[PDB]
Amino acid sequence: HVSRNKRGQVVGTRGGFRGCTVWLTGLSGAGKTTISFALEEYLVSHAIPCYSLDGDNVRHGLNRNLGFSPGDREENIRRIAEVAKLFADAGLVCITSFISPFAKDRENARKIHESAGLPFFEIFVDAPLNICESRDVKGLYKRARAGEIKGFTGIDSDYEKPETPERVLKTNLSTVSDCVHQVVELLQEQNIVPY
Amino acid sequence: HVSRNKRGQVVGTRGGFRGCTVWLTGLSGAGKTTISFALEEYLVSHAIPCYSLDGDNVRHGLNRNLGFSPGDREENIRRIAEVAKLFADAGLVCITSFISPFAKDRENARKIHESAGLPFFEIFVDAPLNICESRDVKGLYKRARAGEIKGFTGIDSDYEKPETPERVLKTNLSTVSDCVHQVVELLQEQNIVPY
Ligand SMILES: Nc1ncnc2c1ncn2[C@@H]1O[C@H](COP(=O)(O)OP(=O)(O)O)[C@@H](O)[C@H]1O
Ligand SMILES: Nc1ncnc2c1ncn2[C@@H]1O[C@H](COP(=O)(O)OP(=O)(O)O)[C@@H](O)[C@H]1O
Ligand SMILES: Nc1ncnc2c1ncn2[C@@H]1O[C@H](COP(=O)(O)OS(=O)(=O)O)[C@@H](O)C1O
Ligand SMILES: Nc1ncnc2c1ncn2[C@@H]1O[C@H](COP(=O)(O)OS(=O)(=O)O)[C@@H](O)[C@H]1O
């Protein structure tokens, strides 16, 4: 195939190979989707080609045959990681917004990127469970409490807090714009995004 | 998310939204890999960001848990189609080089692109089986004849020749450059590649 260095010439304007994955992780309703969109607008506004993977374009498409059992969440996250690696390798900034509950799966995603020489930035989107449940963006928390959903992350299945993420976004203690700026700063420090 | 039309400005220096999938189909050794590489080179050399999906980057990753039974080749091609659609939606020209033996799965790939308003070009890379077997690029035909591979398309499983492909490339009757030109011409007529 054509090399990353050639792809760096034609992907976008700025030149340079800037493929990587921004990997958002955290509780349902903690803010992954919001941050991923606002990051995406920042990136396009600054002429860095990017793409957002989330449940909307993954879960009822590539992964529509997956549910929420531990084996299925692990396949979900495995397939996502492989596809993300393909977008990073194509030279885009790939932003993922899956709860991705289990440390093991996140570290496997990272390993698949590192083996391929692609930067992987794990971003802990950290809000308290009670705050996520009070946001109840989609009404899942109220259904899970009522027993209509089981295996629901945060209530009757575990979220394993990232021990060593590249950034922690405290979404109950700061604005969307501050959270984005924290990630952008990281991409600046890694020459992915111009100052 | 950010709109297709905004993302189209930012993916490359040629303006305009050029996301689409060039879907190559045909027998092992018919010439999919060769055409896809030369097409990728044409696009990158003309400053159009593109990406190639093939067995090398899909089958031992995303689709590493899939084999060659008819159901597995059908799941293989479905997942492939969904990811291709994701690259088209990001604004890249996505080139796939899977044998993809079954018409039903190919037409499902098309439908998944068309439903999303993304161009899908099915490209029949057509050489006679005997010619493919004489090329035996990777030694698959000699292994299949010896019974070490089963279900090997063309020998003990069917290839269903495309009835309405957008182009037919007779790779035994013309050069790589003529065949590529047939595809490039199609992309010009489809406003994917400027005149
Ligand atoms: N700093 C912040 N980051 C992300 N979301 C925030 C923040 N502050 C408030 N919110 C609100 O919390 C909700 C986050 O939900 P969502 O982004 O759908 O979460 P997730 O994708 O992790 O399920 C949104 O309604 C958003 O407006
Ligand atoms: N017009 C043509 N188009 C494509 N390949 C050709 C052509 N003429 C000769 N070939 C040769 O045919 C072989 C096809 O191998 P490959 O492209 O790997 O097939 P596939 O990807 O379909 O398995 C290559 O060695 C290539 O050089
Ligand atoms: N039994 C088989 N039939 C066809 N291809 C096989 C078989 N076993 C292994 N392969 C291989 O299939 C790879 C391509 O398969 P695709 O993944 O292109 O097949 S498809 O039928 O699911 O679209 C070849 O590179 C290759 O060697
Ligand atoms: N049982 C559940 N556990 C966690 N999330 C669920 C569950 N059921 C539905 N969902 C949800 O489905 C989406 C979460 O999907 P993912 O982010 O893909 O989860 S993950 O664990 O496999 O990484 C959210 O809409 C969401 O709250």
Image (cartoon, coloured by chain):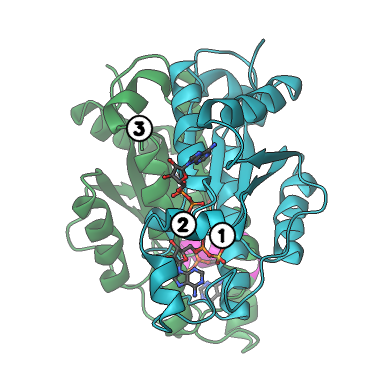
Chain colours: A green, B cyan
**Label disc, if present, on residue A2 of the rendered structure:** 3
Query: Which x, y percent locates residue A28?
Result: 49, 64
Query: Which x, y percent locates residue A25?
Result: 37, 58
Check the residue under mark 3 and report the chain it is in. A
Front of the two marks 3 and 1: 1
Q: In this view, does A120 lie above or below B47?
A: below
Query: Is residue B177 shown to the viewer in this render?
Result: yes
Q: Assess whether residue B99 is covered by the magenta stretch.
A: no
User: Helix, strand or loop at disc 1?
Assistant: helix
User: Helix, strand or loop at disc 3?
Assistant: loop
Q: Distance from label 1 to label 2 (Cα)?
A: 6 Å
What's drawn in magenta, residue-wise? A130-139
Is the C-beta separation of discs 1 and 2 under 8 Å?
yes
Check the residue under mark 1 and report the chain it is in. B
**Label disc, if present, on residue A48 of the rendered structure:** none
Is the C-beta separation of discs 3 and 1 under 8 Å?
no
Task: Judge: label 1 CB < 8 Å from ligand 2.
Answer: no
Query: Which x, y percent locates residue A100?
Result: 40, 66
